[PDB]
Length: 305
Length: 307
Ligand SMILES: *[C@H](O)[C@H](C[C@@H]1CCNC1=O)NC(=O)[C@H](CC(C)C)NC(=O)OCc1ccccc1
Ligand code: NA
Image (cartoon, rainbow over all chains, first blue to last red; front, side):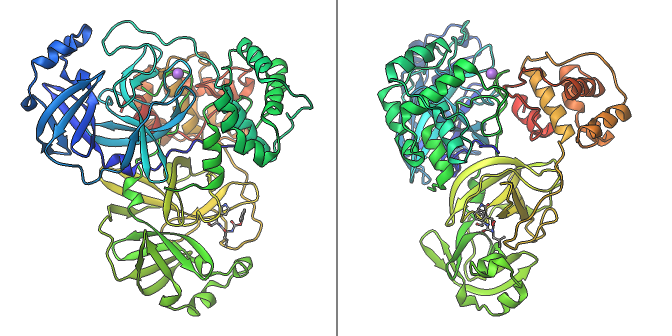
């Protein structure tokens, strides 16, 4: 009586991981075709990180100042540029393991797999969610920057996250693969805090549908609600409002169970207002919010890549 | 670190080295996954069963009636010709005429209850997902496996060497899963027959709960600490009363690094766990969980919190 997080197979991403070093600063890069993508703070000394002028620091760097290694094999850098908070290093070798890929910018609440890497070497894989406050939970240690998050769709890898930093609460923050941070964070060693977080309503609904599919349906009630009335109530419980897109991505689970989305919204509303009354759902006394509607189908359907 | 006080996530090994070994094996209308290492494909022997054979198979009888050509092995789009076959316990070994160039350095190992491993769930020879499991004390695992998942494997990685420890065979009526080592020997008292089977009463992996309590402290949550003290024997008396596994001195030793890192002696953490068992959590959570989590080993915790 449970439902477990499942990461994507990581092999396609493992074949793209390299290490990038400047001075004594080493982090990970992503090698796709003849370009390596990595966090721009690789060009900083530890002291530079306190208050960096990245345009000025990059002016002082030449191609030959960058050590890019696939394992211990050096890839010669033949060009460099900065795009927002990422550095793009052109190399003289096209990665033969490049998968079909896209760069995407994900929404809060969307999940992805992280391939945590150190010195260009993959160490572990785990599933996480972009929190509404634009942080993520999970393990990142010294040397993990440049590790990426991704989804797979058929045979195409959609990269959505590159790791840059850890906040005081221990959660993590980063950019998309165009170097734009998720959230209001900056890549400098300055006082930064994660904002107040909220619960990912669309994902809770997905998980309630997973419960129904598995025969755990005591919480279905006889009410319905409008989306607007539900969104106003949800925010009082520190739950995210639903978008029109959220309603639509729940479509398949609603169809499979025959439970209208707004009826499930009314059932969630009563759980928020009344509590769980000593009961569990899928073995949990807590409402789980890090499975998307897609995660529920992917796991109940056996999708491969 | 591992992500702060709000949760502790399972982390699997990267699956690429195993992905390169997965193939599809078909016999009749029975299809599952195989593991292709050098010139041998390993897979569950019930691939040779019709749906009807599975209800009560005599495997030696079924296998003697099969020829190499009854086995269709596919690596991606390429058929692999089977040139020999043999059975080892509940695993079939298909010799093929092609060596897998992606064979990693590997070993076959049999894991102990309480130990964790990564599962690469596959369907039709294609990787679908990765997650971490523990071998329960009753020798089941809480996996996610559907029809067609058999032959998916569990593994750990050390350096560049893949230690395969599990191959998937079946789902029990309670929804937990059962399988074999790569020598085809089941974990637990189960058989590869489609008949209802119950596991022994499960117990909680005490050393793992303690490791996870240390992870909570590392991530700044100490609310459950006390300073009762306990002897190891007295802790085990309470643990056994609550259907927890005994803690050995050998477990106490393996907790040493986490105890040193946090400044909490192992027996002091035992005293805190004893109070949690006797008093419950009273509606509080630890690392985001309303239950005591027992599927992280001391090694898993150190791996995620410090390296
Ligand atoms: C092998 O692919 C399959 C994996 C099971 C099937 C459903 N979830 C799993 O983990 N195992 C079997 O088909 C197995 C074969 C016997 C000869 C051991 N039979 C089995 O597991 O029966 C239980 C079952 C439950 C739900 C659906 C189908 C079978
Ligand atoms: Na946290």
